[PDB]
Every structure is written in C-alpha cells, then in structure tokens.
Amino acid sequence: KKRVLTGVTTTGTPHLGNYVGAIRPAVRAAQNPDTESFLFLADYHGIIKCHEQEMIHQSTQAVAATWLACGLDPERTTFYRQSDIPEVMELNWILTCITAKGLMNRAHAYKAAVQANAENGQEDPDFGVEMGLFSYPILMTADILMFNANEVPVGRDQIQHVEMARDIAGRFNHRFQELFTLPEVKIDENVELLVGLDGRKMSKSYGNTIPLWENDKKTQKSVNKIITNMKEPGEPKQPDESPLFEIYKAFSTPSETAEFTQMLALAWGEAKKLSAAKINAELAELRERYNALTSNPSQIEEILQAGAQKARKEARELLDKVRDAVGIRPLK
Image 1 (cartoon, rainbow, N blue to C red):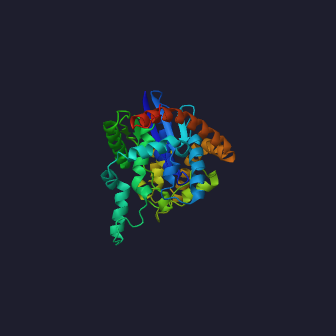
Image 2 (cartoon, helix red, strand yellow):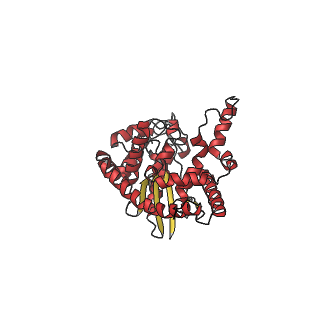
Image 3 (cartoon, rainbow, N blue to C red):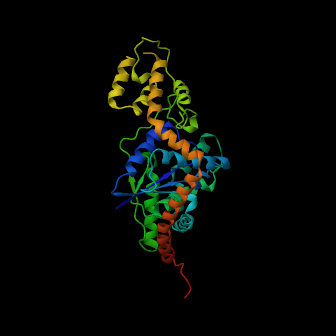
C-alpha cells in the first residue's frame, strides 16, 4: 500500500486559488483506497518568516477548517499538526548530521535570497538570511521520512524538495542502516494555477485574492473587483480579455464554459454576476461546514489531536529504529 504524504502551509487564509489549485483535487485524490493518505499542517515551517504570533494561530485554524470543510476525511486521512509530532524534531537533528552543507547551499529558497541581495546591491550575500530559510529543507525531509512516505504530492516548482529528501535518505541509509524509503514526486498533471483579480497569479503576496469563505454577497463584490476593459454591453469580448473567464471555467463544466464564451461574443457586470453565482453555488454547502467548524473550533482541536495520536504511533516505531541505528541505546 502506497503511503502518500502532503504538507500544507499555515501562513494565511485559503483563497479561491488554493481551492481550485490544490484542495479540491487533493480531497478527491485522498479517497483512493490503494493509498494511505497523510496530510499535515506545516505550522513549524510557518514561523520561518511569519513571526506574527496571531497569524500562525489564525492560519492553522483557517487552514484546518478549510480542508475539513472541503471533504478531507480524518477517518481516511491521518491529519495532524507538525507541532504535535516531537519525533520529527529529533529526526530533524539526526538528518542534519548526515546532510552536506552543499545541499543546503544549492536549495532554491536560499539561492533566491542570495540573488535578491545581489540585485538590491547588498555586499553581504547572507544579509537578512535566517537559518530557518537555510535549513527548512532538512526539516521538510524529516516531515517526509518520519513516515517513510512512498509519494509526496508537490508542485512542479517544488520537485527539488523531494530530491533533497531522496538525497538525505540515501546518505542516512549508507551511513547507518537502510531504514528509509526514498520518497517519490507526485505531480498533478491537470493542475490549474488560478489567475487573480489583476491578471497575475492569485496570491496573498499580491493582494489580488478572492476569499474562499465569505458569504454570497461579499463574494459578489469580490468578483466585481476583477479587471476587464472598456468594452460596453453588446461589444463582443473574447475569453483572453479578462481573468473573469478562467475563473468561471474553474467552477463550471465544459458545457457551461462554452455557453459562457458565446454569451461574451454581454455586459461585464452581468458576466460578473454569472461568475459569482457559479462560485457561490459550488461553495454553499462547504461554507456551512466551514462556519460550523470555526464557530466551535474545539471540534477541530479534537480532530487534530486524534490525528496526532495516530501519527505519533507510526513515528515512534521508526524513530526507535533510527535511534538504535545511530547508536543511541539503553545501558544494559
């Protein structure tokens, strides 16, 4: 049985792009009965940059309620906070000891920070760089290896995370004993990165998001914020003129998408009404479950605690083998 392990960030509230791009297909994929599904909230990766203490907490609750509301089943998926698995932190140090510094030197996030200092005219390549940025790839590797995942769903952007995990696993196996499975990349072949309000990728960094969990009316006003042009009612408009089209398609079947493209060839304001209606219709049931979870967050706490208890039973078994293999053993 193939063990599949997904880490999800906790540094902001999910928006429409997260739902279309990651959450909706991840919940379907997790239903595969041939797979053992693990999914964790990466709340200790969260504090690499996000030192607003209120943020990681609010985001953890928002992200956890979001996945539950969209159908993640904690009876099928082992579902836990990274901060509830102390075994991962011990493994993190063990792996650090067998990881070449060269491997962290070459990691993309660090290199982009170094380049940004060069472009900004900084004489120090490590200006403003903290060790969480330099060393999180070892922590992410521990996240994966602690559960001997066979597959790790990642963005094509993040393939290097799994390669570093495979490299570190192999160095441990060669230095001590072969305890670790080399994890493998899983790419979503049909992933659609959703466009935001201003035509760039929808991103918290850009302030161009459409929120996931606001009511019908507040969603309408957010869809109204999408850029269009000065084409009036009756002027024919092609799908490439406004991010409004790609947004409608992400919440519609190919049939409705084609009837929508023919209506355009129609007023922007009315196209924005049709787009918001389609979004609100799909999210209506998910929003009631989201609002029930967030209105009683101790339901979420209980779920995370039950998922942590499951995860730690697996992590303890392996950690005991790792400790023995690195020579940490009782005096007898």
